[PDB]
Amino acid sequence: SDSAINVMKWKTVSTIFLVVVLYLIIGATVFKALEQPQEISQRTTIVIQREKFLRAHPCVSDQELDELIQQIVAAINAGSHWDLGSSFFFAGTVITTIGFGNISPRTEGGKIFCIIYALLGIPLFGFLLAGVGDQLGTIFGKGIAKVEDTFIKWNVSQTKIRIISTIIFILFGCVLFVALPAVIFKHIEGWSALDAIYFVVITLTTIGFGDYVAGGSDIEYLDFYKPVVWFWILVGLAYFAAVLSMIGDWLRVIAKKTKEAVGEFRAHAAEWTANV
Amino acid sequence: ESDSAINVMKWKTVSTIFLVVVLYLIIGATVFKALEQPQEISQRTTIVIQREKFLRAHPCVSDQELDELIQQIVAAINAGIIPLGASSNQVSHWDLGSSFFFAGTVITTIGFGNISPRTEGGKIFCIIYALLGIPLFGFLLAGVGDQLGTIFGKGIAKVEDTFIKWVSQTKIRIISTIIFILFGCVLFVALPAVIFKHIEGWSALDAIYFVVITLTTIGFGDYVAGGSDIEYLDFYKPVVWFWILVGLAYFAAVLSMIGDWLRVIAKKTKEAVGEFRAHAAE
Ligand SMILES: CS(=O)(=O)Nc1ccc(C(=O)NCc2ccc(Cl)cc2Cl)cc1
Ligand SMILES: CS(=O)(=O)Nc1ccc(C(=O)NCc2ccc(Cl)cc2Cl)cc1
Ligand SMILES: CCCCCCCCCCCCCCCC
Ligand SMILES: CCCCCCCCCCCCCCCC
Ligand SMILES: CCCCCCCCCCCCCCCC
Ligand SMILES: CCCCCCCCCCCC
Ligand SMILES: CCCCCCCCCCCC
Ligand SMILES: CCCCCCCCCCCC
Ligand SMILES: CCCCCCCCCCC
Ligand SMILES: CCCCCCCCCCC
Ligand SMILES: CCCCCCCCCC
Ligand SMILES: CCCCCCCCCC
Ligand SMILES: CCCCCCCC
Ligand SMILES: CCCCCCCC
Ligand SMILES: CCCCCCCC
Ligand SMILES: CCCCC
Ligand SMILES: CCCCC
Ligand SMILES: [K+]
Ligand SMILES: [K+]
Ligand SMILES: [K+]
Ligand SMILES: [K+]
Ligand SMILES: [K+]
């Protein structure tokens, strides 16, 4: 029977799917909870700012303000953006699929090229990010050859120290690729503590909202900064990739334990209810 | 456990790719400023034109405070404001279902980002939500790919039988891969782009563009399906969810297929250089 196996699979697909569906639902309700209020208070005070700009400047008639705002919304569809190096940045947002999109093509040619550039770049960059991960993996693999010797000749031994080693990756990894660069961005970009960490995560997961961008504002940047941030991305993507994947297997583990633990609760209500 | 003889062979391959990437970026960059710098200038001279016609048409406005005004508008437009008087009431951006949409942009890492948290809590949650969701959604997109793969696997069991005429094994692989790309383009690129053109009002190019940008999970968010207030059959948006769920699993294989094509090109070209050497000497 071969449809027997596919019904085993589609059972597993559907349950995950509903987990995702319900993870979204829980998510949605927490975001609306967090953002609906702050959306109201920003919408009442933006109508305050508006009528206060008719009274604090009686020169402005009510009719020609509507015209200005149309002109500004029009110019949010443009904003140099496409200078010799921000177009290099842009090519970066494509092939990493971070895609901040503060900058995005407007020419139909630029869109058509971007389509081609992506279908060829996103694979290509991939191979780099695998090598970047290969080397960086054997770097930390040597690192545990040094730490899995001095702690393994004494106090409590194997099968739990794997749980200690994985902590050292996440802890040192957070420092090198989350903490240290967030501190840098705090000073250089002017972001708060939270915003910098936020920007790290959003960008290294390649979510890349682009509500925050490293380099995006009109500051003096020391000519070493932006290229250090390239290297950070190049390396830090390969880090989160493993980080996300590690979380991946943890879910697999949790899903086994929980599934069989439900089975335990079942087998003890049965023989609790047989007992009359 | 991990010798230096093989890792030197690897770091040789990493570095060459890296410089290919570096150069692919450079070529890219130069084609994009080529395409976009001009149209950035002409929009940016005519925005200074529009400016002076209401710099000096109203000198009573402080005019330091006009450049401050636009700062106050664009800063507030990234939460999403409709600051007007002939439409002062305002549909919610974090309503029941747009926050559901947003949670979608996170765990798929499309991240359009027209909407993004402002609250410190929303940022903190979003960080947690992503580190747990991006793995989770992964599992779904693997099953979604599993089923969809065995669907097309049965499809070729029907087509790899009737085209057995007086046939190779490794050459019908080249016929199969064509029907994946052909039918896949129609189901997941062409047909939905046509839908979007009608429903969203986008041109032909914009729709296809939006498909690709979104299905690769680039997700600039210069275009979004559902983003405006228009009508929305609400048959529509849930169909688009399903399209994404399936279409991500499609591009994943599509991009991966391109992946091995590069592997193949990189083999032929590497050995062709070596031949080009002994044959340019002559
Ligand atoms: C509106 S602007 O585009 O013209 N200003 C800029 C903003 C950022 C950069 C830049 O290179 N930042 C570092 C970086 C590099 C590669 C990648 Cl993929 C992501 C990131 Cl954050 C340049 C200009
Ligand atoms: C002002 S608004 O931004 O809040 N307007 C909305 C915009 C879009 C949607 C929506 O569901 N679109 C389909 C969809 C679904 C899931 C994913 Cl991941 C991507 C996409 Cl395109 C809902 C509201
Ligand atoms: C013989 C020249 C043909 C190329 C024409 C370039 C002029 C600019 C027109 C751009 C039209 C958009 C298509 C670009 C696709 C690369
Ligand atoms: C190698 C066979 C050629 C197939 C080229 C199609 C690649 C897929 C890119 C998406 C283009 C969709 C076609 C839209 C035409 C209106
Ligand atoms: C019009 C399409 C142009 C794009 C062609 C891309 C070809 C990619 C060749 C890359 C060479 C890889 C060598 C790597 C050696 C490890
Ligand atoms: C062998 C060295 C490994 C890379 C160390 C990463 C340091 C972080 C630099 C990025 C700071 C923005
Ligand atoms: C009116 C139809 C617009 C078609 C635009 C061409 C799209 C090119 C993408 C295909 C590249 C392989
Ligand atoms: C789109 C840019 C293609 C760049 C061509 C790279 C060819 C490099 C040859 C290196 C010798 C192996
Ligand atoms: C044999 C696994 C398939 C179970 C039936 C569900 C198929 C629905 C396909 C999507 C319409
Ligand atoms: C060691 C697990 C603690 C993390 C929270 C677990 C959520 C409960 C799931 C049921 C096992
Ligand atoms: C968000 C998780 C809700 C509790 C887990 C429900 C899954 C049970 C599947 C057996
Ligand atoms: C049978 C697998 C796919 C069937 C429907 C796909 C069409 C999506 C239209 C948006
Ligand atoms: C569509 C233009 C491609 C430019 C690259 C030419 C060199 C192969
Ligand atoms: C609005 C439907 C037009 C039919 C598609 C033609 C463009 C290929
Ligand atoms: C945004 C309204 C559509 C909600 C769909 C929910 C599950 C498909
Ligand atoms: C099988 C359910 C997994 C949720 C953690
Ligand atoms: C129960 C309100 C949700 C509307 C989709
Ligand atoms: K992404
Ligand atoms: K993205
Ligand atoms: K990923
Ligand atoms: K994005
Ligand atoms: K974006």
Image (cartoon, coloured by chain):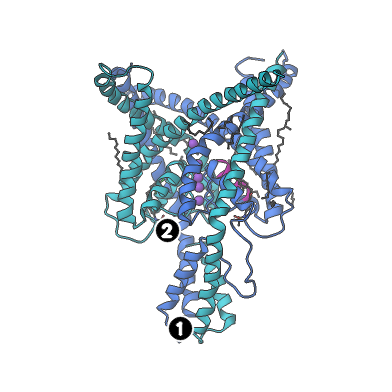
Chain colours: A cyan, B blue
Q: Residue furthest front?
A: A276
Q: Disc count in the image?
A: 2
The amino acid at mark 1 is Val
Query: Which residue occupies 51% across, 79% down?
Result: A52
Tag 1 secondary structure: loop
Magenta segment: B207-217
* Magenta: main secondary structure: helix
Viewed as shown, does residue B150 lie left or right of B70? right
Q: Position of residue A129 (x, y in %)?
A: 41, 34
Which of these two is toward me, A236 or A90? A236
Specify whether disc 1 shares its chain with disc 2. Answer: no
Chain at tag 2? A
Disc 1 designates what residue?
B61
- The tag on residue A81 is 2
Q: Is residue B217 visible?
A: no
Q: Residue at x 58, y 53 (%)?
A: B223
Ligand 1 contact, mark 2 (Cβ < 8 Å): yes
What is the three-letter code of the residue carrying label 2? His
Residue B37 disc label: none
Tell me if residue A3 is in the magenta stretch.
no
